[PDB]
Amino acid sequence: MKYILVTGGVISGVGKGVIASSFGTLLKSCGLDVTSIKIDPYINIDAGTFSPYEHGEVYVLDDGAEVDLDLGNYERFLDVTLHRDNNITTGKIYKLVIEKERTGEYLGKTVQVVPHITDAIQEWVERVAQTPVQGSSKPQVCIVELGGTIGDIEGMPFVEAFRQFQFRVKRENFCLAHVSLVPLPKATGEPKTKPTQSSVRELRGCGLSPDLIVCRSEKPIGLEVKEKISNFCHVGPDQVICIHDLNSIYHVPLLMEQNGVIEYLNERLQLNIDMSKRTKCLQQWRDLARRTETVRREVCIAVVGKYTKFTDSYASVVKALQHAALAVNRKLELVFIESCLLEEETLHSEPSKYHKEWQKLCDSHGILVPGGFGSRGMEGKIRACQWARENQKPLLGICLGLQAAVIEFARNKLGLKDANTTEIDPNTANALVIDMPEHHTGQLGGTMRLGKRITVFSDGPSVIRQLYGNPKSVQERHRHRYEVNPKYVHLLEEQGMRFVGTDVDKTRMEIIELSGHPYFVATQYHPEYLSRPLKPSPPFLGLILASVDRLNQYIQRGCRLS
Amino acid sequence: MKYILVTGGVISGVGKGVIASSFGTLLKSCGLDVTSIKIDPYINIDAGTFSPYEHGEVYVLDDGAEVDLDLGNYERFLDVTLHRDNNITTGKIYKLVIEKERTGEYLGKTVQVVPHITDAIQEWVERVAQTPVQGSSKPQVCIVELGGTIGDIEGMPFVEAFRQFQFRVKRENFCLAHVSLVPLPKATGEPKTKPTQSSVRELRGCGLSPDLIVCRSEKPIGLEVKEKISNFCHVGPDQVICIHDLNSIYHVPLLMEQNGVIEYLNERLQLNIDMSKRTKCLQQWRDLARRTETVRREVCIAVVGKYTKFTDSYASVVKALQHAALAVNRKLELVFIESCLLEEETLHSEPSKYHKEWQKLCDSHGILVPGGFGSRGMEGKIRACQWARENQKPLLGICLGLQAAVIEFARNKLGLKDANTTEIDPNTANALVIDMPEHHTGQLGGTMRLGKRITVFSDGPSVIRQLYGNPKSVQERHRHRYEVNPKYVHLLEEQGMRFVGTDVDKTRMEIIELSGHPYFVATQYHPEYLSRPLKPSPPFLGLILASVDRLNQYIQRGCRLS
Amino acid sequence: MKYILVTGGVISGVGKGVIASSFGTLLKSCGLDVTSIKIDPYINIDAGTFSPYEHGEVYVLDDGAEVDLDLGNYERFLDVTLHRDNNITTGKIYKLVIEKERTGEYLGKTVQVVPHITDAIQEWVERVAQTPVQGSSKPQVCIVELGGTIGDIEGMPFVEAFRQFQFRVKRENFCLAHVSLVPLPKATGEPKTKPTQSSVRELRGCGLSPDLIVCRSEKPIGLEVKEKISNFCHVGPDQVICIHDLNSIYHVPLLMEQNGVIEYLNERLQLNIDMSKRTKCLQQWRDLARRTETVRREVCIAVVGKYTKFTDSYASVVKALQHAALAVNRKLELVFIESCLLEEETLHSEPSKYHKEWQKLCDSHGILVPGGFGSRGMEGKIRACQWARENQKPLLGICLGLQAAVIEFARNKLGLKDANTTEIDPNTANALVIDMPEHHTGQLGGTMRLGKRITVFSDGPSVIRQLYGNPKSVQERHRHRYEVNPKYVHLLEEQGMRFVGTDVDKTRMEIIELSGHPYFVATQYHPEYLSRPLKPSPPFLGLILASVDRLNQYIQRGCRLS
């Protein structure tokens, strides 16, 4: 079995997830099973005890628990699924060592880092290899990657363990794809390659040998720069690949083919390949770019979030909008609006940036508010939700934001100003949204709704049911813990707020709709995880068509993409 | 508060415990409270899950659990006690981090190694400082040491954490005592110092600065060697201290005074000292050497163990015999006899070392057999115990070995060849020694007798009771888990094997004696831990006097040392 | 062409010259040309501007100039010669770079360390390979070694240059032999392997891979130590070779054959070998040990030098006496006597070591005084030379010491107390020994007699001429610069001091003899360089036979070894 190792670089966060994922989807279409194993050098859990919406997201995509967010790029471009055994953290390894010492497995003697730690990491590689995906036999090539940069204490046991794994097998059963960054300030002009030389030198100071020189830059360099890397890094002249800032994320496989580095992996691993045209399939990557960079209608989509610009807490949101806009020929035009600048405190302090966010919201035709962080910015989303329901604007809620929209409907339409959720102010007389935990078999205390959860519909004629082909039982991931109190839901029966989304026990509300509004859908799960370029998410298709008034003609034809 | 840091060196096992302990006992007599904090970089537990008798011992000296064996040198030369909070291991720190992330202490964000791991180590230093010994106020100078060498991965987080702790306080509130080794092969002659130059270079490659140059050698060097290292290490000429292979372990404080390095710590920390003669007390260290290197009677002491030479599994045994031989003017003459080379299989294989171990044992007049390791060498100690009871030879069993002596008495004197303990062969008809665990309040399953355990005497006129001054309740450490079955003890009542040592419930037997024999005491606890140069252990005094026939005259005078 | 690289290790002085030289003499007898290339990381010249007799010697053996002393072990066990191009120093490389920048070779641009220095070192390797010894064709395997330890700044450009040289050729055209040291103090006992682990870690932190694990110790270790090296160093179990302190220097090839590491080099380089018995020749190394460790007559040899013990300034002297004592069955018994402790100032100061050096010299029957250092200890050699000519004691002067013997003959026999050489006190009336430089073609100023110099005999019947077979012109190395004044040599013609050794111009005196004395030969050249185990030096054979009165019977038989 082959193994592809992708170490860190000078920086961590430029886009190393889509670089190592290009080699997996290139060999998957040829007839080779490719698996992914994520390594996290952080001491804390990657997503178990991590912050909700701050410096990351809770990446839960077909898994009983939660793993790192970097596994998203290894599943969209491919077609396989992963489990909790793929993501390996330093904190998880420290839990099993204590259990083995207490029982008695190391002959009662003390353990160190070698050969007591380098051998334990190699054992987890064999357990994932022998357990492939549901619908295969045995993987042939694996994609191993690690987080962080190079030259850290948390990354030393990983390099020492991977240096011995290649000696146990044959020489052609292991490779290395080192990634680097080539900085170029705007005040110098000349590509002074010096930080890259220090990155490739530290990797060679352990026992490894870089084979695939990956350099990240910002513009296509000429030929005098590659001649210096051949002697400074002491590698081959054809192993240096030039990578610049691409326009999107699907242009990575289209760049390595032009440089001529696909056949280098075949002569390094000594394997067979049954190609049809040129290496990988050309009837999928080239045809996808012909539906985006051509004719565009320029759709204006303005959302409200926590930060005024793009960051790491909105990575899975900006990627799902690109896969849903290429089907109806639309251009990605997204602007970030901070929820803190939509309250009465902003107008009383700095009214200059306050009115600027309102000019970009009323002119748009699409509202997609995700979730907040605590009680910071809850009043800003209330004034933005009432503007869409009174001006026939499309509104869609992913998660958490539904709790702030059900309160607004009870104050303007109904008339319950005291109604408030128990998370912000539990001392209230109208407990609309309370905390309803789940007590499963074997679990103690108040757990959280996360994992393999199946939801059951209720009503018949619904705009969300026809998107999935009129089913009866759909399964989707969850992460929310607060539910709606079934005591105060009797008042909403006489109004237009209908409950078309329940659970198994018919005691929790998830998908709700409003009668009379042309497009007002609010749910609780996350449809961006169950999306892919081969088949986008149905909920994200109803929001794009409603922004351009092209939704009524999609159901009459029979829904070609359901 | 002052802090003395003692890092590693070139070698790890030459005797770093007696080097850092010399600075603690020197300032304790002046009126300054000195505490010790042990740092273990090993991943496995230092003594919890460590092997019994193999590469170490279970050091339990006034503590609810067990700590490292290196803490013995910091308690014999001084007069204070330590707890479980002094010994800090890497595995113990990894247990509390998981508890803090699950509850919610690091603001939900992830943690790394800086400043997430360097600040957690400094918090444990303040907890031990605020909790001194029972009978003091607040310590002024601490002795911080760590195991292993220099340059390992397990020692990197410790150097980075200690490099910042000195910046939080003043400059004169922290010091460093770097120890090194100066090798000199017998085929070279010239003191080619080179490994020492590389040890002081790696320590300065982090942020620390060596202050007390400690170099271990084998002979007093001249003046051309000290001037050569001063320019390589870039330190002061008076900071280099010459340390060679001493004769014992109490000659360390007597060596640093002649070099003139005691007053250097006063000008570095800016403290006061009320001395009487010259710095430390001269009426204790100089008077102790006048009772050992003078007149000796040359006593032959031969014991049976696991290895033929000295190692790390018999460190606390060779140190307790030195403190008990200087009171009656004796010379240390101990020979190690392997128990595996005393069975019938060794005689039929290699009889060269078979009769050699018996020749040195029969000429001696004292048997002190400790404990074995599993069932490897149990039949060898049976042949050596059956002769000490017939040729009026003194015998003293520390631990575990008592189980092999009670079976021999049931075969030769009684006549039960089928009697055998349940540890070796549980399928027997005469279960003499079984496994009797203890079920305390809050503990589940079968625990092990270890910690604060108090034993109660039984008989009156006993040779072991008069050594302590005829008490009524004595407390001593334990570690054994197997006990004697109270069903088969009724047969021993009609013979000379009396039970003069029971527990609280009067169901476990620890101290046993034999009638008619001049000196045959077999116990279960370890008297070597409760010993000190100021007052040696009573049990080890009755064995030395019995080898020279000077025991009957010790009780008539009234026991001046009881 | 194959290349064997032998880097440094923990220590640099224990005997690394005979370790790398064992692989050269093993393949030379099979029919493979072996060459040696010495690398000196020191900035100063290895022997040009180095001190005369202090921390080394001026190794001049068949070369126009002088090279390092470490090249002596690569010529005694073998049978080839080297030149000045084999020894490469850092100071010599810094001289050629300045000549290339001034003329114009690097395209006028600046140069750095890579790839500006790693490529220049590889060019000198090809120049020595294309220029073999006089009487061969082309070498097949080379022995490359360097001085100093591992991790120094002076040794960084050498490892980086050798790391790229192996990539230019094939994989089986380069090897590596890392030598380390395993210390073991007498106070520990257990072979704590820790300094060896740090030496092999720094070598792997550059790009190299250790192939031949060489560990130096002091006693044959068991099997539990080699199992730790296989996992700590991450190498093969059969690559670890155990080397302890041998008895002499010719026991190195006899140790590698028993471990079974000779056939490992054949499978690594893929070469052919035509062996007769077992690998190397067994009719030379085994037969040599049968003439030394058998019957010995115990000859007492006492010489006077600068240090009281063996050091680095007397390396070539102790090796030449071993090759001359095995021919007549003698045991090496040499004692070092300091010349500074033989004057009148030492007697008035510390008379303890004064008569001790005279007691060991009078009992011997052979004086072999080398040369001193300046004017420190010149009066001590006068009292030791005046007695050898009166008590029929054999005396042999290597170099420099002849100047102190000609003055003694002019004071006791003649009567010129004012006669003194111009080096110590030039202001004298009887300039016996003056400074007579040589002005060759092209050389300016006063040069030094060193290099290819041919001496011419004078008299006929001489004890030194019959040792070489009565020649007429002999060539020998020199290094002395002071000569005898041809004006005061007319007085010695009437006495027994005859001049049987002149130069070409018949103006310089080198070999002198004394009439009436049984054996009193004083020369100026160094016979220890022109010696080898296959044919020892004639002058060193006449001194051994004179100590046992077995010299008159050696000339009558016809000199079987001339």
Image (cartoon, coloured by chain):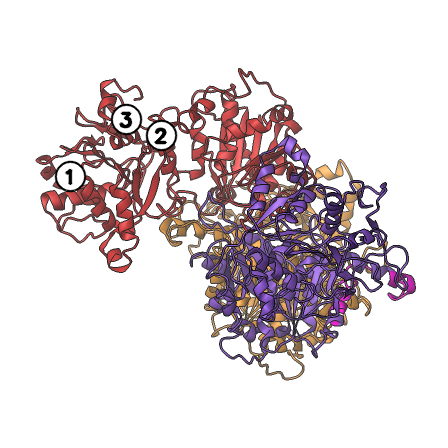
Chain colours: A orange, B red, C purple
Residue C122 included in the magenta stretch of the image: yes
| Residue holding disc 3 | B474
Q: CA distance from mark 2 to mark 1?
A: 46 Å
Q: Earlier in the sequence, mark 1 or mark 3?
A: 3
C489 is higher (above) or lower (below) than A173: above
Q: Which residues are magenta?
A: C99-126
The crowding category of the residue bearing disc 2, from other C-alpha atoms within 10 Å (few below 14, some 14 to 19, many at least 20), is: some
Q: Nearer the viewer, residue C121 or A401?
A: C121
Badge nearest the viewer, 2 or 1: 2
Relative horizontal placement of residue C295, taking residue B157 as reference (left or right) = left
* Label 3 or label 2, whichever comes before in sequence order: 2
Q: Please tell me whether mark 1 sits on a helix, a strand or a loop.
A: loop
| In the image, residue C465 lies in the stretch drawn in magenta | no
**Between marks 1 and 3 in the image, the one whose residue lies nearer the viewer:** 3
* Circle 1 residue: B486
Give the number of the disc on residue B296.
2
Q: Earlier in the sequence, mark 2 or mark 1?
A: 2
In this rendering, position of residue B283 left or right of residue C208: left
Q: Position of residue A448 (x, y in %)?
A: 48, 49
Q: Chain of mark 3?
A: B
Question: Which chain does tag 1 point to?
Answer: B
Q: Is residue B322 visible?
A: yes
Q: Are marks 3 and 2 on the same chain?
A: yes
Q: What amino acid type should be assigned to the residue bearing mark 2? A: Arg
Marks 1 and 3, how far apart at CA: 22 Å
